Structures are given as structure tokens and as C-alpha cells.
Image (tube, coloured by chain):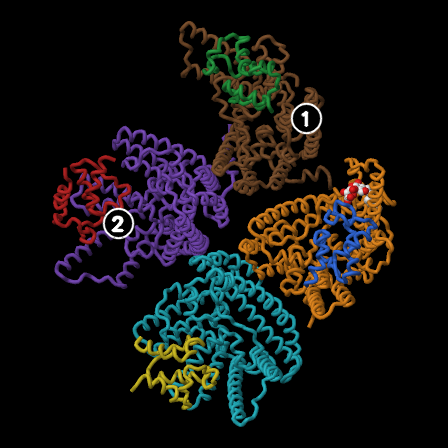
Chain colours: A purple, B red, C brown, D green, E orange, F blue, G cyan, H yellow
């Protein structure tokens, strides 16, 4: 007669995921049995479910504890629209049924990302990490479409999609790799290597998130934002400073979380994909995208880039291959921008990175053909030295930081609005 | 029904490069295949054989060599 | 000051009331489980843990019960050994009755005092309803001669077993002692631990979620609506019937699964208490599923013995009447064990008449099946219609029983209390 | 005096079901022994052996076969 | 210049010896290495010295932290004299020199006990556990007198006298037994048995000192004392209640401390002598003294009672043995009372226990001769029924509790009889 | 000098009873000598052997048996 | 919002290096895993770097929280002028290049020691342990010049120079020995011996710096200083008292720090050079410098004294060995005094120790010559009985205490000169 | 012009004490050379054979034997 259970949900204990050093004490104490049993080639498969559920529910029961209800719907939705495909896959393999199943699987993310733009308030289905969970479900459906995947049990599914360490916003797996890594328990030397690497990641994450990230975010960022707002104009020194500090802060917080997730996943015995591998020494745009947010960029390359270029080349709608590659890059980066959130600045960031990738590809092809012509003429190619590498690193770093300024959304406040 | 001859004849129809004798040599060092170029070959399989190789896990470690491409299509039609 | 107030000042933990109770219990019971892994027992640590959790569960608003508790245990000893030292001489078939009566005396006092003048007797405490059973089982085992020797450590470790002290599954001494002496293997212990974790999870779902939904968010408003509506019967009465019955199952199953998980962590597999009762085809199959520990206890010790003693004297000519009277008396005694009111006795006698009419239906079905086989007629098939009708009627009758047992008819009606 | 002869006489003394030939077959489906009738036979055998066999320990599979009863009564006679 | 040193060693920590439960955490961690070394037949002999010094200094530095200075004198005093005697033992051996060494080695205890009687204030050279430390030193001198002990190093001496667990008021050891138990490290099964007994003693001590001791001493004892004092008169029911409750409280606190000391010594690898072994079920006084404060009573039997009997029987000053035994018992118990503290009530307690033991010995001889005459007369011996044992237990328990009433000092307040 | 001769001549004199025929019997249960009475012998040998037995650690078990007492002087003669 | 970053640095926790014993508790807890892993043949690089950095920054913050910034620049400075000389050494080695590199490497310390004495207050470059850090860098440069060292990575360089246990003011260490000790982990029994050595060093340091140093510096020193200040005059008994009190205070404090540093270094698996090995008992002043501050004295003997002898003798500037030895001793001790700080009394202390050393050498040579003269003339050489050694040690100790009076700076207050 | 004779001549060219016989004997026991006297001989050969021997790490373990120094310097001559 009241429906006040939501208030009851707010009465639960709260625990920020990787938000406090004392969290790792609880996590280590809870995960000791899993690690010990793993040492002896034994997996409980029930204690893991209990610890994953407890820590997921602890993470989600914040101020917006009502999101838990949304989670208890989201799962029930995905199941309904995953098996609905598998039972179909055995019988038929038509393309349009697959498209419909993928769309209905990804619909909750579409609602969460599109309702605030239209309605103005966050939609109900939203919870902490929906944007990093639709990826695994659509990956399962993609694998079923390719025929790589076959019959599987609900246990593997619901322990894969809801994987505890990489729940909130963590490395994005694929089903086949995660399942084969879960089944084959590693050896004692491999387990020891995982443990030492996990401790390294824990300490490095402490450094990255609780010290460097806090310094760059809670100390320099607000004053620079305020000064940039006060100065006004199209561009000025304080907004340049805020763009640099925000880029570094974003990288450090994201890398800290990713290292925490990798450490915990290693403790459970699964090596999740890496997320960052020295992104600011990239020296080139394409080499940047193989270093910044490794998991997400690789996901979009495997499933949204490669499939799109394949389907474009199947119908040969473009005369030349270069135009096909440019179009595929632009569409992939626009979809990445949409995934980040449908506003003006996220789409600007996506299309900007797409144009950057296209320009870099054109320059790379031009340099390759110039080198080929010089070799045909016998002339020595253009030098690659310390100065050239420094120039490449600097220009790529500046373009990346401008992109992060656009993605920050601070340009919306500084340039637009009335303040 | 041999498939090596079909691939050999179909490569030069688009790449305009003689590959009749240069088969076992690494294409990466020769510059014949520029990583992404193999995609243009993949559709060729769909051109006549009406079979699509999965590209979910397709990285530059499994089907790198042309011998792998030749051998994998026969298995992919059964499993 | 030194008084009952001192006892009341002590910390109070509801037995399996919050998950933090469970983390406390897990931390406490980890060392004993690990020690049991290597086939050794600590004894002294077990006694301290059991007593501290017992007193924590008992030192509530009315902590005076603890004092009464002490008397009770002493009382049991004063008589339990008073039979053991008498067992070796001769069983008179009447000293056994006096010992059994004196052992159940605390329970009969606690179940009579509230319904004589105005209040419960002092000797009452939390789990007396589920602790007299162990002592009476001990005395029955003495009478049959199955049990002959035992130390005080075994007796007072079995009777005051912490995981099943409040209201947990009702055990017997022979099985419990044989299970406590012999430590299981390593793989068996791993399976027990995994089952314990599964039981903890399912208990969380059963009692802290489903029980809360069916008891705190639906029961009060439906009860209020039925109370306001009045009359002999109404749709809100059906609503409260179903809601309360599901609440009771989802709470008792949660507590029993908690108790089984803790017992498994202590290395002892206590009897299971619920195996999906609502799938019961007939009434008789319900009692092999609902509160199975207690139901089996009453079947073994109060039903079989009663029909045996009736058969010895050959009081009744035919088997049917003996079975009927045994069923009725057994269920009436179960209702009395719940508490001496009008509705508990009504619940007991209703389950009794349901059981006897189910037995009559089974006998009639067997006779008509034999007639069909003799005449060549095909027996009645049971594929999807008969089974569904049976489960539907059984579940509805059970829910009606739970309505009567709920005591809500006390407020809906106005019969004299 | 023989326990087997006593059982043979007892089973047909009252019911006269002519179950002498049907001994190795399952009596549960024969309608002779059920969840309740077994106690009648137990108390009948108490009238011959005059031994108060415990009932709490009596399991569901304790006396599934007649040979189990025959061996158990002799086992408890000596002890 | 100015002597403010007292203020320097006062603000440093005051961790109680077996005080708060968290203590057993600290010490536990501080004993993790030593115990591990015991498993490998390796004795650190320096780390244990450090932990002993740290915990002794923590225990001593309280409100009366100046006692630390007294300790640094007392130790030195022993080292000044014990070695002296050893040098003498190398050359000669005479009774009077040994007596002088014993007097000069137990003088600090004499000063601590006798100063309040005369002066009225605690003497300077007093600290927490001097009364349980001159026992070790005078025992070593006694052993040197008999020739059992001939050689030892300062390491053994100062790790024996200052043994960390049995320091404040703990089991009173001897040099020979402690040295033998220290040299030969126990094997693996023995060490595991000692560890399990140590944990049993830890939990039993928790029960004895934190629950039962507090209930009997901080709850019932004060109101009973107040009611008894208010009632007045020679004797009354409330003073009987305080007698019983104080007896149980004293036993429980003392047994809790003894169990704690035994547990910590077992963790360090040494089996210190037991103190209490079911003392209240004792059926006779002679059988009582073998169960109540076993370490001290056995010490006085070995060194102060037996030697007294030997010296009395050497000169044959008494015609009969019975008078010698009575005199030896009385003197031994008087010395025990003096050791407890030289006032009226402790001396009364000593004299009372001595008279009780003499009476018990006389009754034992009378029963023996009556039984012998009865057997020689052909009649049945005296009964040994459970009633006789019950009466013996009851009368011994009552006499012990009366003694604890006298020793409690409550008779000094209930009776305003200063002298 | 013979320790055995002194022991046998003192045993039948300190108790005024001829018990020389028993030497290996346990005096703990014999009752001839009490636990605290052993000191009577300890001083006695001091008058004869002029050697004093330590009592610092010898408690209730070190020299309980009579034969051990007899051989104690011989053992101490070495050291 | 943060105001000035210096305020943020100040607000950080500040632990005095080896101050309260709880600092030792924190350090032991932190270094336990490294020492445990040292038993096997593995070492945690990231953990070591993180613990070193955190303890360094904890020591460096506080009221002088700007110094840590001046630390960072300093590090870069060395890396500017160490790797530059490494690259130059790879090809050639000219004397002037080595001279310039050494001068630029010691330039931060030269500025720190010269700015306050020239119309200033305190140079910015200064931090806590610059006096004991440029020694390692100039050691690197001199090793390169000699050609003993050829290759090394940045990890080794910035792990050896920023050694945490020896950062503030610890045993000055060379690089070749330190690197060879860091490469090869010792054996298990050797590690156990190191652990016992570390515990003994901690105990002796507790006695040396927190008790004896306190007694000789915080209770006796101020009253003696006040008495001498009030009394005035050229010299007085209070001046002698303050001389002895301060000298003992200095030795006890420095020995406490050195033993603490050696204990921590042993816990980290590295044997740093020992500073003090029983001073005050050297027969001659020459033996004093093999005992007093052994690390620094050996450093000056190896790199600054011996090289000076070599450069003077190879250029045959002088004619006899004696003059070369004398001038080398004088310059070496003057440079030590300068290293302490450019004032009148530090230079006086240095030159006085130099004069003592040269006169000791002259006396030793004269004694040898007269012994040979009496041997060839048949006369008995001078006796070496106990009295001669006693008078020698008395003279040496008194001269050392006079040196410590001059080095104390108290003569600056008493004379009121150079102010 | 003989290096072997030069080695012997080096020690006597400076002190002129004819210490050729005391070659392998204990120099410390003889007292001719010590921690300071031997440094002159050490530096004497640098100005002739042009060897910059590292003295920064020079401990009291390298040149304690006269035989070792000759082989060491000959080995490092071409190094
Ligand atoms: C204040 C003065 C009095 C103080 C209290 C005096 C206590 C002793 C006198 C009461 C004695 C009666 O108590 C009774 O003593 C007899 C001996 O006769 C004990 O009997 C026992 O004595 C000793 C025990 O050490 C052993 O020989 C043996 O185990 C048994 O014979 C009984 O267990 C006890 O019941």
C-alpha cells in the first residue's frame, strides 16, 4: 500500500568499491579461501558466488540504493534475451533475428544513455555499472552468432557477466577467453606469479588512486576550473591548465581502478585484460588507441570496427578501400562517443578522435608510399631519430589532451551557458 | 578440390602482385599484406564458397600466414 | 548494582537476526572447523563458544530466564542420571513413566502456566520447547536399552548444542554422539563446507528478504483490512492466510538453514528441517516434508510407541481404528506442544483429521485399484490432472491450517480467549 | 523353535495369504507390508519371541528382506 | 643537576601485565618469531631478551613508574652478591658465609616488607614483583651451597631471574629445572602439545580473570564488605558472605594470572611450574597445601621446611620426631606469613595454618594407630564411605575459607583493633 | 667400609622392628616408614658416612628406593 | 583552494627519523615482508621503492616542508651530471672533464655550506641529508674516473643514492660495494645472523640514544652551559664539565643513530659500513680515526687523502715523504671541517685534528728512530707497560674531548668572537 | 731493457736498502715497509710503466703478497 521497500534498501551497509584502504583487508580476508582452494586445483563455485554477491551489493547500496532493484531487473532481462537466442541458434541462423536479439539485449543501455537527454532525469534502469555489463551480454550474443559459442550453463553466464572485480567500470572481457581461463586452473608457479603481480598492483593502485589521483583532482582541478570560468573568452591559460591536469587525473584514477580490478581478479585466479600500458608515450594516434583503455578499444575493434568494415566490403559500396577505412573509423568512434553518453561534448570527442585517426592513417599511407618511391629510386628514406620521435610524442600528446578537454565537459561550462 | 590455386589466382586479381612463387615467405616483411589487408581476402571466401570465417577472436597471431588461411577453411566447414 | 539488571546490561544478540551475527559466528567457528579438518577436536573451545553464544542470545530484555535455564539443566541431570543408575538394576515399566514425566515437567509447566491464571512460569526460557525433546529422547533410549553409558561431557554437549539451541532441528542422542565422535574425511568435509555456504546464502534469501517481504510489507496492512472488514470470512482473510503461511515457511526455513550451516561448520550434520513442503501430493507426504525433524520425532517416539502399546493390550479389534486413534492423539499432542490455546489445539486436531481422512482415501483407492485389476479394468491414471488436483487441494488445506495456527481467527472471530 | 519355521507359521496363521511360495518377491507391492502394517507383524513376533525390540532404532531399510529379520533376531538373542 | 629523571620515565606507556585482552595480541605477535624458532631447534637468545625487556618495562612503568629505577638497582644488587658467593664456592665452603650471603641477597625483600611497619610508607627499593624475584636469587645461592650448581653465565642468570611471564607474581621456579627446560628444545609434537595447552590456558584465563574474577570482586565484594562493616559485632552473616566471596575471588584471580603466565611461558618454550590444581576439593589440609599455590608451597617445602627439619634433627634438640615436625611446620608457616607482609593479620594467617597442619598431623597419627590396633584386634577398619569424604571436604573448605578471611585483612576493618 | 652392613644394621634399629628380610618392598605402601620420615635416615648416614645428601632438588622421587640409597654413597664417592 | 602547495606539504605527517620508538614499530611492520622474502632468492622492487619513498617523505616534511621540493631538483641535478660523465667516460677521460663533473656534482652541497656564511640565512637547495648524499654521487663520479665502474641502470643509481635507512645522516657508502651486496642475496644462516645483529643493534641504540643521550644532553648539558655562560672568563670548571658532557652526548647520539641505521639496513638485507667501534680507547690519535665515524673517516682517507698524496707525489712538487704526508693530513682534515660547515669553530676543529694527526705521526717516527738508535747502541727500547698505554689513552681521550668542545660551538658563545 | 730484471730493480731503486732477498718474506715483520712506506713503491712504477692502478678501492687485501702484484700488473698491462 506504500511500496517503501526502497527505503529499506537504503538501510543496508555501504562500501565504496576500491574506495578505502580498509576495503582491501575485507577483500583479502574473504578471498583467502578461494585462493587457498585454487592452490590445490579446487574451485568451490559457491563461495565465489557468495563473496561476489556480498561485495556487489555492498558496492551498489549507496545513496542511490534503489539501483539494486534495477540490477535485479537487468539480469532478469539479459537472461530472457540470451537463451531466447541460443534456442534459436540451434534451429536457424538468420541475420535479422540476430539483429533484433542484439538490439533487445543492448536496449537497457540505450534507455540509460538516451532518457536524460530527452526526459532530463536519470532513467530507472540505470545502476552503477550498466555501461560495462551490456558489453559482455552483447559479446555472448555475437559469439553465438559466429558459431564460436555453443551450449553452456547458467552458472558460467551469471558468474561471467556479474564478475565481481570488474563490475563497476572495469576491464571488458569476452566469454570464450574468460571461460577458458576459469576452467584451466593455473599451476603453483603461475599462482605465485599471479599473487606477486597482484600485490604489486594493489600497492601501485594505492599510489595511483589514493595519492596521485586525489592530488590532481581535489587540489588543482577546482581552482583551475574556477579561474578559467572567471577569465572567460574562447581560450586562455587557466583552461589549458585545467585540460592538462584533468587529463592526468582521469588517467591516474582510471589506471588505479584498473590495477585494483586486475589485482582482485588475479586473486580469484582470472587474468582480466589490461587497461593501460604507458598511454602518454604513444607517439602516434593509432599507437595511442592500442595503449589507452585497452579493453574498450580492443572490444570496439573486434566487434564494432571489424564487423562494420567487413559488411561494408561485402557490398563493395565504395570504390576505394581508403574511403571504407575512413568511414569505418568515423562510425566506430561516433559509436564510442554515444556509448560515453549522448551530449554535445561526448559526440564531439568521438568525431574528433575519428577525424584524428583518419588523418593519421592518411599521413601514414602517404609516408609509406613516399618511402616506397624513394626505395624504387634508390634514395635513402626520411630519417627516424630522437628529434622525430620527440615531435611525434609531443604532437600526439597535445592532440590527446585537447580531446580530453572536449570529453571533460568543462568546455561546455567555460564556452557555453552564460557564466 | 584444391583451394591453394584459387587463392593464388585471386590474390593478384586485386593486389596486382605476383604471388605464384612467393608463398612461404613472410608477408609481413615483404609488405604484401598490411595487417588490415587480409580483410579484403576474407570477403573473397564469401564471394564463391558462401562461408564466413569468424572474426570475433581474429587477431594477428592465428591466421597471420597464408598457410593458416588455406588450412583453416577446410576445418571451418565441418566444426 | 548486582541484580537482574546486571544480566540485562549484557550484550544481546538475536539468534540469526542480522548478517553481522553471521560474521561474528563465522569468525568464532573458523578455528574449530580448521582443527576438525585435521581430525582433532578442541572440546574446551567448543564449550566456551557455545556458552557465550547461548548467553548472548539469552541476555535480552528479560534475562532472568538465564537463571531459570540453569535450574532446568540441573533439574534434567538430577533425573537423567537418576534413571541411568536405575537402568542397570531393572526396568519396572513404571519408573520409566515417572522419569519421563519429571523430565517433561518444565515443559508442561511452561505450557500450562500462561493458560491457567495470567502469565508464563519463571522456569520458561528461549528454547525450552526444543530442549525437552533431547532429554526425553535420552530417557526413551535408556528405556529401550539402546544407550547404556555416557559421560557428563557428552550429555551436556548434546543437550545444550548451540546451533540448535534456540529452536533448531530436534536431534537424538545416539545419532548425535556417533556423529560427534567420528570426524568425517577431507572431501566429505569440503562438501559439508560448500553445503554450509549454500545454506547461508539460501537462508539470507529466505529469511532476510522473502520473510521480510511477506511479513513486514504485506502482512500488517492485510491484517488491518481484515480486522476492519469483520464478518465470518472475507477476501482479506484469504490474503492474510496465504501471506502468513508463506511468511512462516520462509522464516522457519531460513532459521533451519542457518542452523544447519552453523552445525556443518561445527562438523555435525543436524537433521534437515524442510524439503520443499508445498510440492506435497497428499496430506501424509506433507508431514515427511514440513518440519521434518519434529515430525519424524513425533512419528518415531510418540506415534509408533502408542500404536505398539495399543496393540499389546489388543484394545481395538481392527487395524484401522488403531491407526486413526494413534494419528489423532499424535497430532493433538503436537498441537499441545505448540501451546495450550484454542487455536493450537484446533490446528493439531485438524491436521489429525486430515491425516486420517487421507489414510481412508488411500485405503479406498487401493481397494478400488484391486477391484479394477481383478475385473481387468485399467487403474486410474495420474499424469497431469489428478496430481495437480491433489497438490492444489493439499496446499490449500495446509494454508487453511496455517491460518488457524496463526491465531488470526482470535481477532477475526470474538470467541472467548 | 526354529526361527524360520516360526516366521513361516506366523505369516499364514492369521491372514492365510498363501505367501509361502512368494517369499523372494517384493512384498511391498504385494499389499502385505506397507508403511503401517509392518508394525502389526512386529508386535505379532513380539508375542512369540517375547523380546522388546527397540523401535527408535528401527530404520526404514532395517527389515526390507525377511532374511534381515531372521538374522537380526538371532543376533539379538545371543546378546 | 636537578633530579627530574622521575618525570622522564613516567609518561611512557603503561601496558598492563595480562590486562586488557588486546595485550595478548601484541605479545602474541611479539612471540611469533621465538616460537617459530623453537620448531627448528634454534633459540634466538637476543630477540627474546628484547621482548622480555620491552614487556617488563611496559608492565612496570605505571603510576608508580619510579619503581623502574628500583629495579635497575635490585638487579645489580643480586649480580653484586650472587657472583660473590660463586667465587667463594670455588675456594671454600662454610655455613656462616653462606648464611651471610643469603641474608644480604634477601635483604631487599626484608626492607620492602618491614619499612611500612616502622616508617609507614613504601620503601624506595620496591617494585611490582620483588616478592617473587628474591626467590629465584636465594634459590640459586641455595643450589650453590649444596653443590648442585657450579657454573653459569650472566645470560642464563638474567634470563632466569627476570623471566618475562612469571615476573609480576607468577610461578616460582628453580634454576636447575628452568635451565634444563631451556637448553633442550622440545620436538615438534611436544611443541604442538604446548601450543594447544597454551591456547587452552589463554581462554581459561580469560574466563577466570575477566568474567568470574570481576563478578566476584567488583560486584559482590564491595556491598558485602559495606554491609558487614555497618552491621558490626564480632561476627555476622554479611562477614561470612564476604569471607566466601573473597575466597573465591582470590582463587579465581590468582588462577587466571597463573594460567596466563603458564600460557605465555609455553609459547616461549618453557614449562613453568603449575600453581593451582583443584584446591577446593581438597579433603585435608596436608592435601590442601599440595593444591593451593603449588609453586610457593613446594618452594617452602623444598628449601625452608625440609632444611629446617634436617638442621633440627642434626642436633637432636627434641627427643621425639613429632615435636620436631610440629615446630618445623609452625616455623615454615610463620615465615610464609611474614613473606606475605609483616602485619598482624598475615602473621595470624601463618600461625593459623601452621596450627591447622599440626592438628591434622596429630589426627592422622591417631587414625593410623587406631586403625592398626583395630586390625590387630581382628575388627573391621574405619569406614571410607562417601559421607566421610564429604565431611572431610566440607571441614577443610570451611577452615580454608576462615584462613582466607583472616588473610583478607577485612578483620582489620571490621575490628578496629590496630594492635 | 660397607654401606650395606650399616644399612642392614640401622634398619632393624631405627624402627625397633626386625624387617631386614624385606629390602625391595615399596615403603610407600608398606607403611613401615612415612614420606616425611626419610630424613631420619638422611641424618643417620651423616653420622656414619660423613656425607650429606642434597635436598635442594631431591624430592619424593630421586632416592626413594632403598637400593638406590645404598648405592648413593658409592655413586657420590666418584665425584 | 589549496592556497600554496607548501601548506599542503606541511600538513602531511612528519616522522622524525629514529625518534620515538613507535617509529621503529612502524618501520618493523613495514619492512617485515622484505626481510621475509630475503630468505629466498627474490626481492620486491616496487615494495622497496614505495617504502623508501614514503619514509623519506615522512622524514622530510614538517616545519621545513619546502626542502622536499629542493630534494627533487637535486636528484635531477645529479642525473644531469652523472649520466653526462658516463657518456663522456664511454669514449675518453680527460682530467679537466672529470674535475668539472665532480665540481658540478658537489655544487649543491657547496652552495648549501657557503650561502649561510655569506650574508644570508639558509639556501633553498638544502634538505635533511644533503651532507650525506653528495658523497655517494661524487663517489660515482670518482669511480667512473678510475674506470672501476662501467655500466649501471637508473634503478641501481637511484636506489643506491636514495637509500632510505641511510638518507638523513647515515653511514656514507661507496657504490661498487653496495651494488655487489645488492645483487647477491646472502644465505639463510647468514640472514639469521644479520637478524640477530639487527635486534642487538636496536637494543643498543635504545640504550645509546634514548637513555644515555638523554641523560647526557637533556638533563646535564643545559645547567652546565648556563653555569659556564654566567661564570664567563677564558676557561673555568663549568667549561670542562660542559666539554665532557657534550662530547659524551654527541658520541652517544651519533652511535644511536648509526646503530639504528645499521639495524634497518640489515633488515633490508644490506650490510652498511659500521660507524663506531669503541672510540675513546685509541692509544694514538691516528687510531681514533679508525674508530670514530669510521664510514666518513675511511671515505676521506680513500677518496680525498690518498688521491691527494698520489697527485702531490707524482708531480714531485715536494722533496720528502714527511712533508707530503703532513700537507695531505692538514688538507684532508681541513676539508672534513669544511664539510661540517663554514664557521670559525668547525674549521678550528678540523685543523686541530690535522695538527694532532701530524704531530702524532712525527712522534711515532721519532719513537721508531730512537728505538732503532738504542737497539744499535745496545740500549733497551722504551717499555710498553700498562702505565704507558694508560697515559697514552688518557692524553688521546682528553685531546678528543677538547676537540669536541671546539666542535660544539660553545666557544663561540663563551668567547663571543666572530659574531 | 729486461722487464723481469726491471721488476727486481724497482724495489731497490727507491730505498737503496737491498731488499731483494726479502722478496716473499713478511714485509710487516721485517719493518722495512708499512702502510705508508709501501705507497712510495706503489706510485714509483706508475711514472715508468704507465699504469693507473685504482687506489680508490685499495684495501688491505690486494698487495699483501709480493708475488700477486707482479702477475696482476702484467695481466693488466695489456688489459
Ligand atoms: C584450625 C584447626 C583445624 C584445622 C583443620 C583440621 C583439618 C583436619 C582435621 C579433620 C580431619 C578429618 O578429615 C579426614 O581426615 C582423614 C584422615 O584422618 C582424611 O583421610 C585421608 O588422609 C590422607 C589424605 O591426605 C591420606 O592418608 C588418605 O587419602 C586418607 O586417609 C579424610 O579424607 C578426611 O575426611
- Disc 1 residue crowd, few under 14, some 14–19, many 20+, Cα 10 Å: some
Q: Is residue A336 left or right of residue E65?
A: left
Residue at figure coordinates x 15%, y 40% from the top left: B3
- Chain letter of the residue beneath label 1 in the structure image: C
Confirm or deny contact between disc 2 and disc 1 (CB under 8 A): no
Query: Which one is in front in this view, the residue at disc 2 or the one at disc 1?
Result: 1
Q: Which mark is residue C87?
A: 1
Q: Is residue A216 left or right of residue E314?
A: left
Q: Quadrant of residue H25?
A: bottom left
Residue at figure coordinates x 53%, y 63% from the top left: G198
Is the residue G163 above or below the residue H4 in the image?
above
- Element carrying mark 2: helix
Q: CA distance from mark 2 to mark 1?
A: 97 Å
Q: Quadrant of residue C271?
A: top right
Q: Quadrant of residue H61?
A: bottom left
Is the residue C253 above or below the residue E200 in the image?
above
Amino acid at each position: 500500500f506504500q511500496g517503501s521497500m526502497i527505503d529499506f534498501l537504503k538501510q543496508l551497509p555501504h562500501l565504496e568499491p576500491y574506495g578505502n584502504p580498509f576495503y582491501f583487508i575485507y577483500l583479502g580476508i574473504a578471498l583467502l579461501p578461494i585462493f587457498i582452494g585454487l592452490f590445490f586445483k579446487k574451485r568451490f563455485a559457491i563461495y565465489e558466488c557468495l563473496v561476489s554477491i556480498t561485495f556487489i551489493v555492498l558496492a551498489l547500496t549507496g545513496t542511490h540504493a534503489s539501483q539494486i532493484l534495477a540490477l535485479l531487473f537487468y539480469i532478469v532481462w539479459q537472461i530472457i534475451w540470451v537463451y531466447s537466442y541460443k534456442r534459436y541458434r540451434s534451429q536457424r541462423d538468420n541475420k535479422w533475428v540476430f539483429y533484433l536479439h542484439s538490439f533487445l539485449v543492448v536496449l537497457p543501455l540505450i534507455l540509460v544513455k538516451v532518457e536524460p537527454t530527452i526526459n532530463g532525469t536519470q532513467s530507472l534502469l540505470n545502476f552503477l555499472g550498466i555501461s560495462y555489463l551490456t558489453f559482455r551480454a552483447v559479446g555472448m550474443i555475437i559469439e553465438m552468432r559466429d558459431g564460436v559459442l555453443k551450449e553452456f550453463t547458467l552458472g558460467e553466464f551469471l558468474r561471467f557477466m556479474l564478475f565481481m572485480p570488474t563490475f563497476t567500470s572495469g576491464p571488458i572481457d569476452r566469454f570464450k577467453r574468460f571461460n577458458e581461463d576459469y576452467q584451466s586452473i593455473p599451476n603453483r608457479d603461475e599462482l605465485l606469479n599471479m599473487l606477486e603481480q597482484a600485490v604489486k598492483y594493489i600497492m601501485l593502485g594505492f599510489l595511483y588512486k589514493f595519492v596521485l589521483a586525489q592530488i590532481f583532482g581535489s587540489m588543482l582541478l577546482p581552482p583551475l576550473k574556477a579561474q578559467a570560468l572567471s577569465q572567460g573568452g574562447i581560450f586562455n591559460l587557466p583552461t589549458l591548465g585545467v585540460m592538462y591536469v584533468y587529463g592526468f587525473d582521469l588517467f591516474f584514477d582510471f589506471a588505479g581502478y584498473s590495477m585494483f580490478a586486475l589485482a582482485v581478479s588475479n586473486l580469484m585466479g582470472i587474468k582480466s585484460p589490461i587497461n593501460f600500458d604507458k598511454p602518454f608515450i604513444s607517439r602516434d594516434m593509432k599507437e595511442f588507441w592500442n595503449r589507452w583503455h585497452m579493453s574498450l578499444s580492443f572490444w570496439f575493434r573486434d566487434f564494432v570496427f571489424m564487423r562494420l568494415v567487413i559488411v561494408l566490403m561485402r557490398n563493395k559500396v565504395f570504390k576505394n578501400r581508403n574511403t571504407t577505412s575512413n568511414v569505418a573509423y568515423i562510425i566506430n568512434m561516433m559509436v564510442m562517443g554515444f556509448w560515453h553518453g549522448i551530449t554535445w561534448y561526448y559526440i564531439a570527442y568521438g568525431i574528433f578522435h575519428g577525424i584524428g585517426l583518419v588523418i593519421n592513417d592518411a599521413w601514414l599511407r602517404k609516408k609509406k608510399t613516399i618511402n616506397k618511391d624513394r626505395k624504387k629510386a634508390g634514395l635513402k628514406p626520411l630519417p627516424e631519430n630522437k628529434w622525430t620521435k620527440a615531435l611525434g610524442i609531443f604532437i600526439t600528446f597535445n592532440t590527446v589532451m585537447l580531446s580530453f578537454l572536449i570529453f571533460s565537459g568543462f568546455l561546455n561550462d567555460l564556452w557555453f551557458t552564460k557564466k | 578440390m584444391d583451394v591453394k590455386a584459387e587463392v593464388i589466382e585471386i590474390i593478384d586479381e586485386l593486389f596486382m602482385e605476383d604471388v605464384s612463387d612467393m608463398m612461404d615467405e613472410d608477408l609481413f616483411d615483404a609488405g604484401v599484406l598490411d595487417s588490415m589487408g587480409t580483410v579484403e581476402l576474407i570477403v573473397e571466401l564469401e564471394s564463391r564458397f558462401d562461408i564466413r570465417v569468424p572474426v570475433s577472436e581474429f587477431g594477428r597471431d592465428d591466421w597471420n600466414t597464408a598457410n593458416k588461411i588455406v588450412e583453416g577453411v577446410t576445418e571451418l566447414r565441418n566444426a
